Length: 104
Length: 102
Image (cartoon, rainbow over all chains, first blue to last red; front, side, top):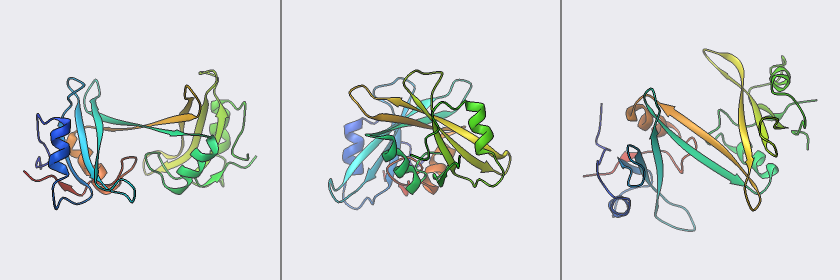
């Protein structure tokens, strides 16, 4: 039972500044109270890519009724074909990678 | 294209996906009956408990064009949440690697 990642009442902007300080690697993270949704938490993560450089992504952690938590993501695509290609590469949130179209 | 099956019932889809020979990750997309104008992505999956089974995901039409899919992960505790994403990004921007320092 570690709770080193729990920061309690910390604001979104404040978590961003803390996370973006020198020496924190990609995938540095913390969990904090949600500022926008009472009773929910937020998972704030430091990430990096070629274009934006260091940035922070926040994910809402909501309460299941009858106990526990969940995270939701929405992935948008221009076309179904683009969705298929994407999830053929990595599972990224689906039960598994798309492998082959069902034969007819 | 060849993953599109049109007006295929949900149970029928499961039936086809669960056909002996199709590997884990065999998939198709079908028109929704429950939600007009939407599609469902049906995938053949497997685990230790259930064995071969099928998951369905709604693909809904965005206003002003394009499509979205929603994925969702559930946990008993924040503790197992953190452990799940330390192992695999699984939908997030990247894996959790280290708690921010105090």
